[PDB]
Image 1 (tube, protein in one colour):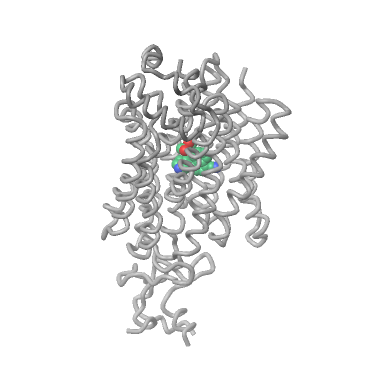
Image 2 (image 1 turned 180 degrees about the horizontal axis):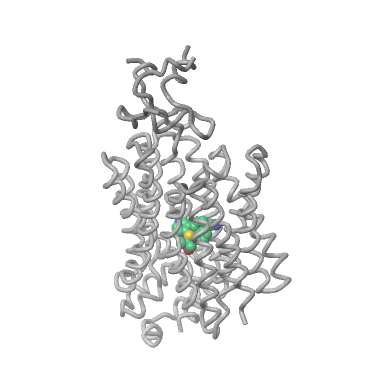
Length: 472
Ligand SMILES: CC(C)(Sc1ccncc1-c1ccc(C#N)c2ccccc12)C(=O)O
């Protein structure tokens, strides 16, 4: 009887739009704390400290103390025991600290904790830890909102994000920074899950397409917001503070939004449900049918396809979260990137969807994975002087991968006995989230050659997409 009550109280109107505007804005900043691990842990050019240079012909002094490296650069991990003045065999690891290049970034976490050379694996692990935190927090919060409400959990998760972010920028050692970020990730996952549930709960009929389109648009704009904010603040201790502070301001205003009116009924909190419904009616201005509500009415109210979807979600999560966090290897000008991604994404997603869906439902699913995977794979062959071509290929690949989610979210999930889609989208989301903690771990394989990470990162989407043609 809840849909009839919602029709009696509203639908579309004013409040159902103010709630969307008030809830979408936190998603922009939520995106900022997931892709922030691209301007915070940025690796500049690091050389070895020398007693000759850098105080107790600059070019000759640099050439005599540091042996030449393989990639046409001074060596980043070794120095000469004694100035080899024979240069008009014996090398010792750096023992006086590195010297970094401060020309685009002032202080990253790499600069402050020397995560270079031998201690290199720790950098692709500080991201897998965050994704494991998101995975854990997206599973714990599921069993903590059906008993504590759907609005209180969001309000407290805002405060948790704010406090954990404001603390994580003031730690003196790596292990604690790898734990407070875990807490931030769990709280962010809770925020996203509850925002989606609240967005759908209050809306009917015109709820499926538009509201879930709004969330994807929010993420796409959050990417541009991340780029713009990173363009301004250059340090890393003043970036986490500036990104985590707005969540406290969101927490204060989050005390006025009404709670879900469908959860209040199944628990017996009829009186407050009535208060919430009448309050919503006044904002919606449809204060004509609300006189009907007199407690009693609310008292009466109170396999192959599945595996294919599993693999598609896993491939999307794997490739996207392994590629979007290393944009220093897809080209240059990191600030210009991370902003063209969303601007490409929205036109690309809309235009690709509109044209391809007319071919068929399976064709759109197939062409949204093979195309970006092949675009990424065809990036190795390009020589390292056509910067525009490789940058365009990478941007197109990421934009198409972003569109794959939408093309597999509301267009897909029908490939089942077709009762309701929240018993399948939620199952796919656990695979998508569990396919990202196995993400940046592939980037640990930069040794044994450097082409292999990109090769795997392009092959996996291609095989996953080509397996979708085997539906029967
Ligand atoms: C776990 C995923 C699949 S990814 C995600 C997790 C945490 N924070 C942000 C995103 C995210 C990033 C870029 C997107 C794009 N384009 C996007 C689109 C839809 C949903 C999430 C994202 C989810 O959240 O379902």
